[PDB]
Length: 324
Ligand SMILES: CN1[C@@H]2CC[C@H]1C[C@@H](OC(=O)[C@H](CO)c1ccccc1)C2
Ligand SMILES: O=C(O)CCC(=O)C(=O)O
Ligand SMILES: [Fe+2]
Ligand SMILES: [Sr+2]
Ligand SMILES: [Sr+2]
Image (cartoon, rainbow, N blue to C red; front, top):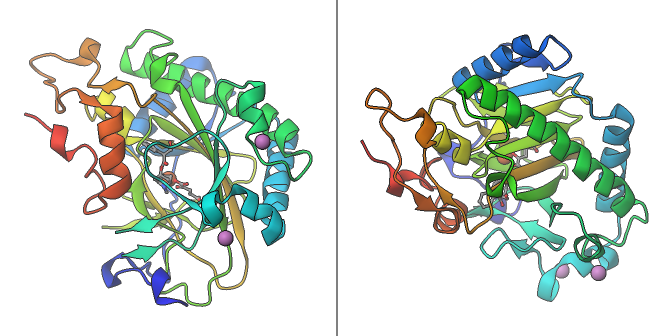
């Protein structure tokens, strides 16, 4: 592989990462209180769990994976239409909601990944008109998927509210206003020992729902485990923003993606979180002398700039705001 994609020795993935047998798989059609308790335990102990019987149509999940794979099969001449000034966009502020293809790495090497990203909320003609023109059915399918994934995310956030003792709808406001859909394409890699599909990270936002069909996702528990792909499940990743708002009562998910020498992989990640204008702080309702705030209030925009640039540590984004 090109030296551009060679990860530092210490960040390279071990060849035989064991299956995460303790990754919670939570049936959302259990009794209400059982679902609240199981989600609460997973959030406190792991920060990553899967949800099944989640009420999002399996047919729509399959149709969305199909049109996302069809997009990445498009020829160069079509993909160039999403490359501003002839190259992929960077994950940097301002992060626009119009569809673009993105490159990503650490500042230095590149991740073995192409990412299509666009905003999904609120859905209006202006936003959907800025989405991919091809495939023809992308806009129709992903509009429906967007609404359904948001519905499921807001259900999970209200289970989280009951678990924390926050009023229902606590996150149904500026804290969930941005919905970025990242479709990740991992082409086959001639040397998986040297490369990463995605470097180890927290998702910086509030909560992320990840749809996957194939292996490659790994979680840090300095031990890495493999997250079993369940094609009809969503992987729920708690973000660094939720870690801060819960005053570390919940864990954030630290995860990475490894490359494969034989086959490509598409994942669909729905990133829900605050507007860039938001102030982030530990929920005052949960604070006391027994539970003092571990973070001072901060600008999400200021956090965002550090989070997207500084990868010296997983929580480099929030280190400046740590107190007590
Ligand atoms: C693998 N990388 C990680 C996670 C996804 C991908 C791109 C980047 O994450 C984002 O762009 C998200 C979008 O909501 C973001 C942006 C600013 C603040 C909080 C979150 C870093
Ligand atoms: O491809 C995956 O399974 C993970 C994607 C991811 O973590 C991300 O886009 O932030
Ligand atoms: Fe992620
Ligand atoms: Sr180009
Ligand atoms: Sr357009």
